[PDB]
Image (cartoon, rainbow, N blue to C red; front, side, top):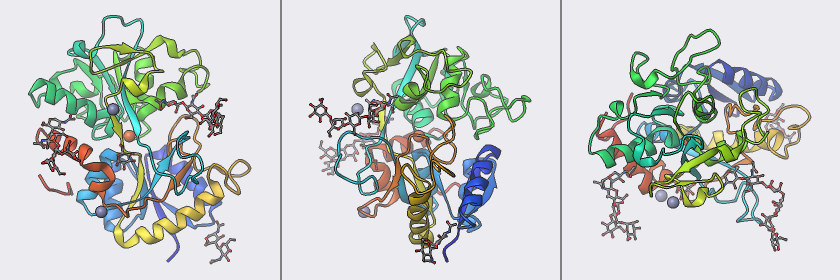
Length: 341
Ligand SMILES: *[C@@H]1O[C@H](CO)[C@@H](O[C@@H]2O[C@H](CO)[C@@H](O[C@@H]3O[C@H](CO)[C@@H](O[C@@H]4O[C@H](CO)[C@@H](O[C@H]5O[C@H](CO)[C@@H](O[C@@H]6O[C@H](CO)[C@@H](O)[C@H](O)[C@@H]6O)[C@H](O)[C@@H]5O)[C@H](O)[C@@H]4O)[C@H](O)[C@@H]3O)[C@H](O)[C@H]2NC(C)=O)[C@H](O)[C@H]1NC(C)=O
Ligand SMILES: *[C@@H]1O[C@H](CO)[C@@H](O[C@@H]2O[C@H](CO)[C@@H](O[C@H]3O[C@H](CO[C@H]4O[C@H](CO)[C@@H](O)[C@H](O)[C@@H]4O)[C@@H](O[C@@H]4O[C@H](CO)[C@@H](O)[C@H](O)[C@@H]4O)[C@H](O)[C@@H]3O)[C@H](O)[C@H]2NC(C)=O)[C@H](O)[C@H]1NC(C)=O
Ligand SMILES: *[C@@H]1O[C@H](CO)[C@@H](O[C@@H]2O[C@H](CO)[C@@H](O)[C@H](O)[C@H]2NC(C)=O)[C@H](O)[C@H]1NC(C)=O
Ligand SMILES: OC[C@H]1O[C@H](O)[C@H](O)[C@@H](O)[C@@H]1O
Ligand SMILES: [Fe+3]
Ligand SMILES: [Zn+2]
Ligand SMILES: [Zn+2]
């Protein structure tokens, strides 16, 4: 009945889950997979219960029957009275970021540049930006637009993996899990910060979180915001402060998914679990925090205040919204009702 097998992607996430599992008295247990796609398979098979997922993977998962349960919620300034759990989710701002010194570089001079993506099939990293780029260009040749990239999940032998580093040993080049140096929001941003790339497709929170002494991490301590710039679709360039008026799209929050025959029970264990290890949780600061991993967004983005109830008991199409659901479907014409397993 009341035991949840969570699916960790990669070895860094397995160690946070094991610790979570240590402190939960087996209320949560951990399966492990190499890539998000594999984890979705494990949950389909019933060998794992649930996992937190970027909107891009939620669309894959959805075609395969999986259902969103709870969603991540960050610090908000509208909806002050409402408790985090009952508070509506705001989404997040996909942005294209560049280095200020890289003068001249505009959304209209991206062709043949170098790019940093979070991973293939994710929202801010891949689907919005590449979606705009296929539309604007009239061609599915997205593999020929940037000269070199790090798009974790693309063919290791391809130009789309050229700029990825792999792990400390140089192994696992381009793998779509935290072992890649330039995987996910932080890695894609680092990718630009180290001047490995000309542009990084991350979200707004990422720039702020890793700049102005916020990360303390070796590669990020000396980073200042004012050395960065966003690329608007109006061909302009703005400071990281004008995010609301210079973004590519608003992205539906990452959410936990499960099989629907389990959602009721996944939902219950987790609400309890967060009362214990969440932002103001009984045993967070002292013993263990579910929502902290030191700029590494492991299992959950470090900016999650809490996971929140959904309300409108929404399906996956409704959760992602008809706007975004069309964006992906158009883009998948390039690579029409499926379940890719
Ligand atoms: C892109 O992503 C960035 C990073 O994620 C994000 O920046 C982050 O924003 C959040 C909030 O959205 C910041 O957190 C906040 O920081 C402050 C200061 O350290 C914290 O302290 C205060 O918290 C108060 C309690 O919530 C807050 O009250 C708020 O509510 C009151 C009343 O409801 C209201 O206050 C107003 O004050 C007026 C002046 O006297 C007064 O006349 C008026 O009547 C009014 O009541 C405001 O609504 C207020 O927001 C205080 O205002 C303080 O904020 C606070 O708890 C919270 O922790 C993050 O620090 C920040 N990240 C970084 C790295 O700085 C960007 O904003 C994102 N960009 C976009 C476009 O979304
Ligand atoms: C890449 O490029 C493709 C090709 O253009 C693009 O796909 C297209 O996206 C469009 C926008 O997302 C789609 O148009 C949509 O809007 C209409 C209108 O409905 C909306 O407007 C009304 C009034 O303003 C609102 O009240 C309503 O809430 C909607 O927001 C949609 O169809 C409408 O449906 C309503 C139902 O209430 C009817 O009453 C209307 O008469 C009308 O039929 C439509 O379903 C779209 O959501 C367009 O459909 C879509 N084209 C194709 C072939 O799929 C991608 O979005 C681009 N991608 C990226 C990344 O930009
Ligand atoms: C594992 O989960 C169970 C279910 O919530 C917890 O046992 C309940 O905990 C609450 C709070 O202590 C009690 O009020 C209930 O009486 C307990 N029993 C039930 C309802 O079965 C337990 O606390 C969790 N264990 C850990 C270590 O997190
Ligand atoms: O406008 C963006 C919105 O898109 C979707 O409906 C999401 O479910 C919601 O979190 C987000 O606020
Ligand atoms: Fe995302
Ligand atoms: Zn907008
Ligand atoms: Zn509905």
